[PDB]
Image (spheres, coloured by chain):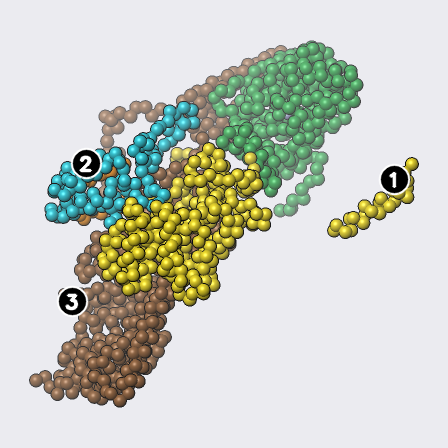
Chain colours: A cyan, B brown, C yellow, D orange, E green
Amino acid sequence: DPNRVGLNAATLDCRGRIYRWLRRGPFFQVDNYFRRSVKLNRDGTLPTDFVHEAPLMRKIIRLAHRGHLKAACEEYRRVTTVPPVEVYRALTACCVPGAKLADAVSIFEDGDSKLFYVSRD
Amino acid sequence: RKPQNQWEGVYYYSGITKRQRHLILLHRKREREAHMRSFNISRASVLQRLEQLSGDRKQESLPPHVRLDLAVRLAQHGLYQQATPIVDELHHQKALHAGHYALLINALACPRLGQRILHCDAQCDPALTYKLLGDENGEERAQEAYRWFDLALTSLAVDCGHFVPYLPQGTAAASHITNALMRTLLTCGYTHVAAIPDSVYDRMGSMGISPTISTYELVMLALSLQGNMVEAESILSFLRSHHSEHITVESFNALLLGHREARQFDCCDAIWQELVDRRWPRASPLTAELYLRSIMDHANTPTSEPLQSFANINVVEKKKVPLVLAQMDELGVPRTHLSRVLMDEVEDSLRKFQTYRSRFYEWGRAVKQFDFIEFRRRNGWLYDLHLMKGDIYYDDTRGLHDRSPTWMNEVPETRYDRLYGVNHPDIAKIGIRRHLNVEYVNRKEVVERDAALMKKTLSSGRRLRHRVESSR
Amino acid sequence: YHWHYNLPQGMERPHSVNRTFAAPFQSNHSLVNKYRGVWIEFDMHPAFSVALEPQLRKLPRGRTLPKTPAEEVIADYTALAPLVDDEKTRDLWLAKVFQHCAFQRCGGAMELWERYCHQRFTAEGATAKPPLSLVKSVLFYCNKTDNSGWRALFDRCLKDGWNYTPLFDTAQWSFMLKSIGRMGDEDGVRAVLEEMLDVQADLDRVEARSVVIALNAVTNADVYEFVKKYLFNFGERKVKFLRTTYSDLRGHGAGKLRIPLKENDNMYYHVCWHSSIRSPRQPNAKIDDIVKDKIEKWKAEGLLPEDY
Amino acid sequence: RMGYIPRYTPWEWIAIQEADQPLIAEQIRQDNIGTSYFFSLNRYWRYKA
Amino acid sequence: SYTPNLTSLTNQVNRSERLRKWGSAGVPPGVPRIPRLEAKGIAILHESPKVILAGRSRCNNFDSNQYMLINKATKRCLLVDASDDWPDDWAAFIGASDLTLTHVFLTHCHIDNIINLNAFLTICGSRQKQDEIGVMWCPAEECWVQNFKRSCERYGRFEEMHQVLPMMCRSLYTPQHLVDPVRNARHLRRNDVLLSAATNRATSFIDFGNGVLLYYIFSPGHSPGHMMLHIPTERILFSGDLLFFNKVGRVDLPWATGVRLAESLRLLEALPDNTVVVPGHGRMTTLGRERRENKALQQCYQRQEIGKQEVSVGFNEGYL
Ligand SMILES: [Zn+2]
Ligand SMILES: [Zn+2]
């Protein structure tokens, strides 16, 4: 659904909502924006299939197949949804001709436990 | 405000549900059935192979290598009685050689029955497998291991027929069969594992057979199972002095196993820290299994000098388990190569002593603290241990008052405020005004208010004194 | 009252609260990494998997659902499956098209069960035993398309039959109870809920929208008294969440379901009564002879006169 | 004794306080691969640098 | 308040009423000691050629008062309801005025009266070292001296909990201890007066010296034994807790009867209007002012006129 993409927020009306804002954790805005956004669906598939950032996922695979690792890492920083399995397949294949093991593990460790095991492939 | 307790720990979830502990017990029983099913299928296959080659090959004599292949497969599955007529005719036909005798005695230790005993009966304890293999004909397999050793040395004298008065005792085949004999005698009972460092080792010395590294490691493992650690470390001390190039992992595996049986847990820590320090020979998963099981036996051990006045003290030894598992990641030891019985107790220690940075920012929230209190209030009968029911060494005559000027430095504001009327005859010594002696923040303002109250009281008392006697 | 500063500031006594009370992890939020679906346990031999690789490509694998329409994978199993001479390979392949037709809701996939697997598993006392991956796929299929063929297969999984009910997951029972409440089988709800209690399934972790649908279809009188004693088997956290979901599914949030619920208010008033109960506060023959002896006395006393 | 307060906490009382609180997994700080020169500062936006 | 039995712990409204009164704490904060700050000095209230009345207002956080009668001729002083948070000014006042503390009068044995009574006898008894001080009280207050420890738990007076009261000790009206023949500071208290409830104008008095008589009046209703002090020569009435400025004592405490309090208000209607009534709490008044502008006395006689046989008057919000 492309037209229903968006998250509305509140206004902090009453005093009891102000005290909750002053008692929130260190990651309360970025955590609740992450869980109101993309999550595992009813059938069990990934939330990878996102329409608005679909050509951005094509750009990283296009950059990781030509050997541009740093530019593919720069466009990976701009993602908000869960990236597909094909970008992790292309990013780790970009690290092998330069023997960059430290970059390839951090690519896998980003999507292993944080992004619903999309890099566990 | 009432103060909070700073020596009270943070309420956090370290435990499992009754369904999960039942589901762990239910799943572990299924794979114990699977290893029991896997052994008896292959045991029936080699017994069907035996009766096929005995019935249909009744008069046709088999080639000696087919009968040799079936004899080791019978001895591996714990069927030693079905294999001794096969080896007796192969020795009589002189078809067995130096490597064939060492193959048969190594097969007599049954490394297929021990695989069933490990996963099902011994609860994946590698020390308990030697204790349980000795019951299934331990004395009976030891006599045939001694008989096949006599069959081997008789055949080696024929096979060697200069160095003529020193044959076959100086060959490589004599020690290989002797190493095969000690490996088979380890699987036997306690009477035969005690004979390995004393009786078999002196017989090897009296025969003049040069030992190898596998000779000393089985003797060290034999002294490990007896519980004698002063002799087991002495053999590796002989190996540390003379033959240090050939020391493999199994000498360390005997010492990790041996101090676990003797319950000297401080010694088995130092062996593991030594193996992390040298990093050669490589730590097998048997090293990580024998060391982590020594932690869990030390953790479940109760103490008796405090007699558990508050709680169990030895449970703090499970805090080393995230340290050892971090060391296994750099030693190249995979943690997935651990047994299912140990892995449940390893993850038991992990959910009790491990936290991440994302959880540490959220574990102290009052919602999770008050859920811990209510869950203790609702069902505390299910999870509780209580509900089940100058220089001083050259100083001797000290130099006092060495004219160190305290007036060059400035500490002038050391004024002290004492209570009014200490030696006054009208003011009593004992009283509730004695509690004013312990007051620090308002020390100046209280005692000047106290002195103003006591001066006006003694003034009003003595002016009442002069008024009454002047009127009468 | 306090501790003075010149006193030694030692710890008075240690507190071991986390080792006396071993608490399991309890969060109000659900697990973010769970599969939330029915697993098939695809365990094919690694020679037919690369052989049938253009055919298994359009089939749902682990956490992947291709959008191939169901009439093509039926035609692939119609032609190529008689070519492979292996029994468990065809059964595992048939479990995938039963899973593929379930996610796309194709009602015509029950002909594949009667074509191949009915005659050797569920016909005339068949002694052959189907694999677990095939029974899980067709029960997930018949519950998704609301097919009435689940009853002959669920009766085969009992302790005298195939005995596959201890191998069912908690998500399998959630999709099971949703279809019976949609079709409206009163004895179908009771026979499954008696099976879930006999098998010791996770009753507190079934889907709450699935339970309130299966409880909404209870209209018979004798099975309604079964629900009254079965409602105590849930937890106190679960039974207060069954009230809030059943009140919203019949109220404002009625659009979450594909078909609307039917109005069963005697189940609605009992669940609201049972949730308030678990929550904290915030001789006819001998009596009939007594009355007849009194009316006999009152006619003798004259209090009950005759006609004037 | 009549008022004995110890100036050293006993070994039993230290071991109880250590056994009640867990460890932080990032305190071991072990590293053997190296620093990710390209990706570690450009990871996912929730857990980013 | 009371003993936490099984039904008080299993009651939800016990956990709810403790939330309404005290918020999220649930435990009532006690009545603490007045510190050496915010405390006043001893005032000379009345000077007469016979006696001298010296007093101090608001000496407790119960807002109680501390008074002392000083006889000019005998140099003998007498404390009335000895409850001061600092009985060290009172020891220095009698030490600097050449006075001898002989007895302590107690109207009733609530915690607003005997909270520092052991402190009064110890500090003033230590000064006469360089005959002990008596206690004059009524034996109907025996039920309140048993619950003195219970009252100290509810009002946070933990330091005066483990203190045996001096009136509980063996006096001359008690059997004596038979000690081993192989110590009478606490074994026997010879100076002790037990007042009788049969109080009359003839013989129920204390001879204070030089011809002034302290007529004690038994007037229950706020407490089982409530002994007022009346000095008819000086027009002074120590009502204690019976009558205050524009209010009377509480009846919502145990052993407090509303119909006994109304009979206690009727037994002071023969006294003149210029009798300056000196209460245990608050400001002093006259008896003529309370006969005109007190609604508790106005309701007491209005119910009597319209024919109420059991007239019940009494406060539920006020002083203990
Ligand atoms: Zn009172
Ligand atoms: Zn009072």
Image position of A118 (left or right of E52): left
* Label disc, if present, on residue B246 of the rendered structure: 3
Q: Residue at x 65, y 44 (%)?
A: E179
| Residue B465 location (% of width, % of height) | 57, 16
**Is any part of residue E162 visible from this angle?**
no
Tell me the subunit letter for badge 3. B
Cβ of mark 1 under 8 A from ligand 1: no
Secondary structure, mark 3, is loop
Please determine whether, in this image, residue C111 is positioned above or below residue E117: below
Q: Nearer the viewer, residue B428 or A66?
A: A66
Q: Are marks 1 and 3 in contact (CB under 8 Å)?
A: no
The residue singled out by tag 1 in the image is: C304
Residue toward you, B193 or C138: C138
Do the numbered discs 2 and 1 sit on residues whose CB atoms are within 8 Å?
no
Do marks 1 and 3 both belong to one polypeptide chain? no
**Residue type beneath disc 3:** His
Distance of mark 2 from mark 1, alpha carbons?
103 Å
In x, y percent, where is residue B19?
A: 44, 53
Q: CA distance from mark 1 to mark 3?
A: 121 Å
Q: Is residue E213 left or right of residue B90?
A: right
Q: Do labels 3 and 2 touch, CB within 8 Å?
A: no
Disc 3 crowd rating (10 Å Cα; few below 14, some 14-19, many 20+) is few
The residue depicted at 60 percent of the width and 15 percent of the height is E283
